[PDB]
Length: 189
Length: 189
Ligand SMILES: [Mg+2]
Ligand SMILES: [Mg+2]
Image 1 (cartoon, rainbow over the protein chains, first blue to last red):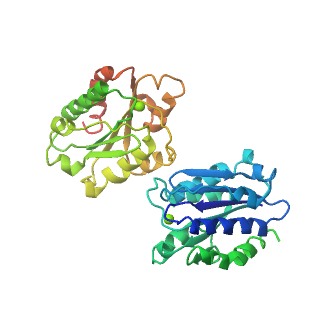
Image 2: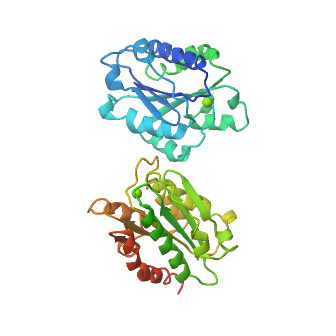
Image 3: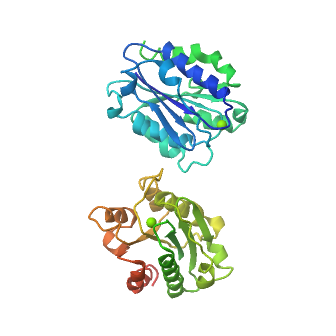
């Protein structure tokens, strides 16, 4: 499995909630680390940060090591654009990504996609094509609406009830590790 | 005929040539005027300025006065996003666009698309579905190759012969002036 992480570095996320976020991620990588599993991370906002590719991870496969040194981005939310860059570069052959393997994407966001030229319509359709499975963790009040949830039901793979986890706040992410974990195991064993 | 212009305001355009382009536009809108014609203007770079809308035109049908105050935006070349907006905002009924009218668009730019999240692959198609006729004018030494002009043909309608025009300097736009004018009359008569 080519398991990649897309995390929201929006400056709407207070340093420690962002601290937490970061700890969540380390933990799941260690928790899902099979032998042939690869990992990659990028930090998206208004600027886009590749912290590491599959290709790298295999010559230093240590979640605590690589997760540790990340720096927040603060800008706004270009989720769609972020998606396009995952598919477009993370999941490319020269980046470690292996062709006969499962493509998995886990997104973590705290708001709605603000000020993005692209849309889900522009990026969604090409993610399916190469067949990327998408699981979305949405965090906070921003997601309590009868429309905010739509954006989340949308970045997800179908069915959405099994791909979406609407948590209450940074702390409260520890609460779904077993879930998010077992769902990603079941599709490899 | 709902006729709209997209003028490149990038930083590579020196101020006297930016003034030359502003002249061209005023003039052509003059020459192409008829009682049923409406004109719209947008300048793009990295930012996007809608100078006058279809229905605001019909509030002060005066090319010349309307073009006078236009100051240069200074960005870089985000041409696809520009096409998008032209198509999404200007040929919008609420911005005065008429249901049974023709939709002609004239693009003028001194460069290659650069650092644009969108591809022409994401805009050309919306432009076709909405029946938008595109003419491209590529000014300067950027479209100097059997390659960069290939940008022009992609943007422009088919056959490419008829919809593309390239001139060496701004000061030469005056040369394709009469040939353009006519092209845009064979649509209507
Ligand atoms: Mg946020
Ligand atoms: Mg330029």
